[PDB]
Amino acid sequence: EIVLTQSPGTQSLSPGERATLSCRASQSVGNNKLAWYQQRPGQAPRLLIYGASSRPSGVADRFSGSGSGTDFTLTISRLEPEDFAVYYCQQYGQSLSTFGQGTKVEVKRTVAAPSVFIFPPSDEQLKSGTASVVCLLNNFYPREAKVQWKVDNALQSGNSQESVTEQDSKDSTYSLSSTLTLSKADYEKHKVYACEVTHQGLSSPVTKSFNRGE
Amino acid sequence: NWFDITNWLWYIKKK
Amino acid sequence: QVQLVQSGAEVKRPGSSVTVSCKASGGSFSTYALSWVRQAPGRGLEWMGGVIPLLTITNYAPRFQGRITITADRSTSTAYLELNSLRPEDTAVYYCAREGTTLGKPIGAFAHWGQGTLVTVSSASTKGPSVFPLAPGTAALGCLVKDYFPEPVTVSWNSGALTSGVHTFPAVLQSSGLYSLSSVVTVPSSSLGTQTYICNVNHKPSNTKVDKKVEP
Image (cartoon, rainbow over all chains, first blue to last red; front, side):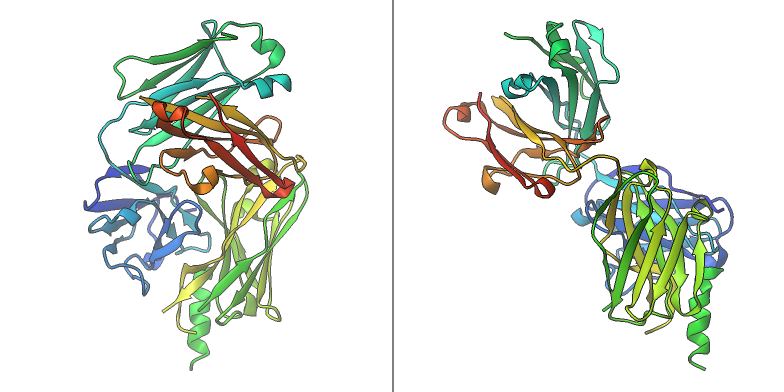
């Protein structure tokens, strides 16, 4: 089985800049049967390059493929706004076809620290016997951020889930939301609910908190 | 290579 | 032009078998290679296997050999993927893909893609969400769309009139096997007394269509 390595998995680049994406194979790819695909969220992949360097009709010529053997490169001569997407390489020089893990090309912008908000459970939910506490990390860059829940200063584990938005099309930031869920009975056992946030843009962790029933 | 079969097929269905 | 149209999304119980179909039009069906590729939520592409219809020659990836069947029917220009002994790990969007041409010379690489079929492997039953407010310089407010199945839900604000500063998060899969989703928006603090904020939630499978006013 030929292993295709795409490293790094993410490239942060500015609009208009050149991009070079590498695909290294664990052994020589037969007859340079190497293809590149682009994929946007909510869409099927789209073929950009086949046979290492051939471009289908309709694909912009700012995309070019090169290389042979084990070393392949996708070059984007000048990044357009629509070029920020995920790129996959694929070899089909053996009957067992394999894909690389993909490289996300994302928009580089200035560092932005998250604005943090915490939300107590609604009265409506509490009436139903469950308590969800929500922590919002809004409009930050870069994507790496960490959220820790603390309940009466006790670090929580296993009772929260989080998700992150796609990079914003207008200001190129990310947002993250974490939800802590407890039974109403357990929620009522504690006083202080807090989320603690770390990020490159913060010199020290930010904590937002509330006191239950206040 | 299974991915070469249809190319072969295309060729022999011309000649 | 070659168009591939797949069957619709399906929820399958653990251990069951799923059949996904892909009907082609606009080209030659029999002499071009048709593959299946899947993509688990938040993950990369994975080649599963393919078929050359005319020759009835299949080619499966080793890790699916013994668990999948790919077949073709030229009378309807349709290809089928069977995947058996389903597990949660098999939850993915399944794409059919046909090789491109230079009725021309085939190129092997996948130029033509179906729209994808979401297959969700779960024991969960259809359920509509509850919609809870996230009550509010800049203020943040939102809605928590909790405990629904299956995907998807859609959320808008003020019947689509409010999009600036809106963030709707990817759904999370809870231990219950139900999904939860949050949508938030930032607004001027001063607007909290003068402007109404309503999140419009749609979950078609349960016919849950809720318009929740979010108040301080």
